[PDB]
Image (tube, coloured by chain):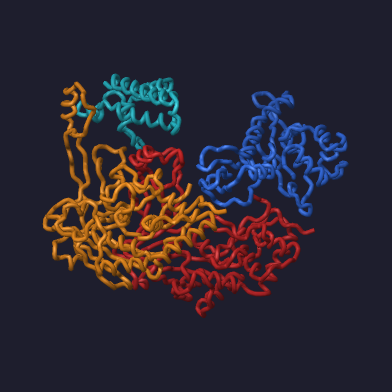
Chain colours: A cyan, B orange, C red, D blue
Amino acid sequence: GQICDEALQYAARLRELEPGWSATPGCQLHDAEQLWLDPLRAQTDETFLQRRLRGDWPAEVGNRFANWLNRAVSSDSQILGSPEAAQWSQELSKELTMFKEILEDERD
Amino acid sequence: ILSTASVLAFERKLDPSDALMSAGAWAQRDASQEWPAVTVREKSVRGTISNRLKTKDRDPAKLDASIQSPNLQTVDVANLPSDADTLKVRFTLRVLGGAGTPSACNDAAYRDKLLQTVATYVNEQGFAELARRYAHNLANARFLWRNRVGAEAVEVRINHIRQGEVARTWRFDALAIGLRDFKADAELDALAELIASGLSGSGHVLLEVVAFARIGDGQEVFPSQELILDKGDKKGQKSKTLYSVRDAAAIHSQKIGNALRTIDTWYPDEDGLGPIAVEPYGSVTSQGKAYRQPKQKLDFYTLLDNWVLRDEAPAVEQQHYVIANLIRGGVFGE
Amino acid sequence: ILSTASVLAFERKLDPSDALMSAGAWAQRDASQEWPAVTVREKSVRGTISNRLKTKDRDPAKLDASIQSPNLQTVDVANLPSDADTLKVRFTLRVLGGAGTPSACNDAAYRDKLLQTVATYVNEQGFAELARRYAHNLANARFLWRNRVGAEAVEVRINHIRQGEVARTWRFDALAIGLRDFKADAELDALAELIASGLSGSGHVLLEVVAFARIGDGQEVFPSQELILDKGDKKGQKSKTLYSVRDAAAIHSQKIGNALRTIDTWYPDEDGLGPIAVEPYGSVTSQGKAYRQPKQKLDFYTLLDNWVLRDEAPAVEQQHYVIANLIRGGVFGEAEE
Amino acid sequence: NAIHIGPFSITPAARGLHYGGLPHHQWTLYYGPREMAIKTLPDSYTSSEVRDEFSDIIAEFVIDARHRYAPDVLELVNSDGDAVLARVAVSRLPEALSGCIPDDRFPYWLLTASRPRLGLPVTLNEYTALAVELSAPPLAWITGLLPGEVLTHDAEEWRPPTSWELRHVVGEGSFTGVSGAAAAALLGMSATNFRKYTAGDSAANRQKISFAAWHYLLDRLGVKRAS
């Protein structure tokens, strides 16, 4: 949960420093990282960009965060043999669901 | 004392090339050298949601809101021309020999034991059963995977090319020879004898395989599908990319190789399904299931370990399966 | 009273370049100057589960679930065009000479003792056995490693190039000359005299070697394989990279150099396997084994220390091996691993 | 006024400077001839402060040398392949190894911990014999930092260690952490006769240690097994 909170705080830091939400070279994750780090409403991502620029895209950002958490916490094959592995997997799923709900509630 | 080597690698025999696609009219196939190649093109595809979502969702309003997004994609496609009904798929297959010798190995004693085990396999019988099954898979156009399904007439021309010119020709009806059982025919037995002479190291075999499939005017052919990145947008082949050699639709050579070694009719679960491709824990990706499951003692690794270490030579069908796996090649090690 | 020098370094002789690959049709081998290069492409690969498994695995649920989620890779591949059946491989080779003199050495007494030992080797016989074996390994196209296996016809054209134009030409049938035994032939022996003149310091030898291998239309050729560095990659990257020089598939120069010095037939294990590359503790990576293990006294360092320090000259084929290792070059001395 | 911490030496730069108004000197830390670090430390620093200014670099050197020259590890496993039953750090390999995947023809196997495993079938009595013969002492990694001609068993090729090589194992700053008095008591000598070995130059009453005393000292310090 602390890690999830840190990620939220990290996202808040991006929200502190997003004056011009312009894509650049090396921003190839801008469909999800540019969407989860989406700045205030620009003219390019206008009302016609309600699925491209103003798209509420919490599922792809949640999948990327779940992949990063699974890379940082790689479960063993017999790690779920006791209740600790199932509790850790359920806690990771609940943290991803809470982050997705907080992103969808904050997605416009 | 003797144990299996920790590294043990075999180069593949029966190397096929990438299979190129061209198009033409039927009965023009004897002048099918200037036939134009099948070009891969783009098109747009917009469709309503069709995949099974989480059912019993009591919100039809969000469902209708998702339906008003046409989720536009760009898709690679490859069709025949409107004035051509025949797809011509051409490749070459090289048969080398030396199918027992590894390319890399740790133990020399295990290497010599394996070499003499394959040597006793060759002395008991030649490669004639395996070359017969490979010649059957050459005879029917199994390497046309979805370009064979629903074809009116499939014809296979196989040229043995000894010098720079053609040394022999075989002509087959691929719909006469089934994809199910392994038959006998004198031209097919001669082709199997040539493949067996290549696999036995007594010659150098190069074959040119041409397949004509009468599909229809402007119908859709199926080349190999590439891998697509997701960092792009909904354009630029966002859903499907098709494999191509230079301005020509083509098939991956490993697809041709998979369809060539679909000879395994000895797996213990069933025999009414037909052959599968030779694999350790012989498994097909379509069914998501493993025949030659290692709880049963019929996978490639336990059979080779019992044959080489404990001298427990298996049944002759399983010996055919083990030598077919060694012709397939692989990385066998811890 | 005379010990080995603590540092000792020999620059290599027989420097090859990177071998460049082009493609064309056979019997256009004389007009093979505008042959287009073999390019390196990418393709997609889906893989089964065809490796050994642990006893923690092989439960049918786990094996079937692993077969459910497959592995997807991108692979670098190099092929001939579908209208060309001949691979052409071109490189150049410098035979330099001065093989006894180290490029760095600590002891002066060890230096002139080693220099006069190589001098007595050259006075007793020339480089003609070594140059004969090197000319053999040029004549059979052993620098085509996997591109020679299963080939219909291999032909080698060697132009000795003195000024900016051709001074001499050799034409060899590389499938006729074996990879097993070292024969005798007048053109091959004249090439050996040229290489021995280069190794002796009596001249400047520059050769251009071209190989034509009749493989087949559209078949796979095998360039050198690079080393891929990825730490935490995103599930479907490249798993195989191929060496290329300016969008032309190529073989590394040390690969050609390893195939050139495959002349060691005098290792004490056997001789029915064939020649190996000259190495200290002469070892092939494919067999994972070290012939001339130092527990026998036939590795490079005990042979050299007996020949130089204690004047125990070995057999003449062991002398051939030690001089071939000096032509190979290396870091010999107390930079020990 | 140089400072000697085992094989390391910290020397000042023989003329200071004035940094920030205060007088300073450049101190250089060497590991023999190899220059490891330079710092600019002020005057009115005691030698203890100069010592634990460089103690961190010395500790990183010790960690790197201990990880780099670690001895090999053999593993006793059962017939399935996983479930390591025992481990043993060996200084040599059992010489009958040849690349192996364990099967169930034998219940016990001895594999290398390196990944292309080599292995041998054993029966818990020859495993004990191999572990007795080939085991590594707890400070075997210091043998990585030694020239090897001072570590050989052949007396024709052996040469005695210099004072800098002797300070790797003997001294309060050495990697064994054993003083000269304790190392003299290990050899059955006096402290002065043993300090005769640790002078540095042949003029200042320094003799070289003998073959038997050097190899017995490496045995008793737990550096080389020396059977």
Quadrant position of the N terminus of chain A in the picture: top left
Count of labels in the image: 0
Residue lying at 71% horizontally and 44% vertically, measured from the top left: D146
| B328, above or below B198, in the image | above
Q: Nearer the viewer, residue C27 or B276?
A: B276
- Residue B130: image location, x then y, percent: 34, 61
Nearer to me, C75 or B328: B328
Q: Is residue D70 above or below residue B325?
A: above
Point out the residue furthest to the bottom here: C186
Quadrant hosting residue C217: bottom left
**Relative side of B98 to C315, left or right:** left
Quarter of the figure with the C terminus of chain A: top left
Whole-percent x, y for residue D224 in the image:
72, 42
- Please give left or right for residue B79 compared with residue C131 in the image: left
Give how far across and how far down residue D55 sits, in percent: 67, 30
Q: Quadrant of residue C126?
A: bottom right
- Asked if A102 appears above or below C265 in the picture, the reply is above
Depth order, front residue of B223/A29 = B223
Is residue B248 something one can see in this rendering? no
Rendering quarter of residue D24: top right
Q: Is residue B188 above or below residue D100?
A: below
Q: Residue at x 23, y 57 (%)?
A: B21
Evaluate whether residue A1 shows in this view: yes
Pinpoint residue B239: horizontal percent, then vertical percent. Answer: 25, 41
In this picture, residue B301 sits left or right of residue C114: left
Q: Residue at x 17, y 37 (%)?
A: B46
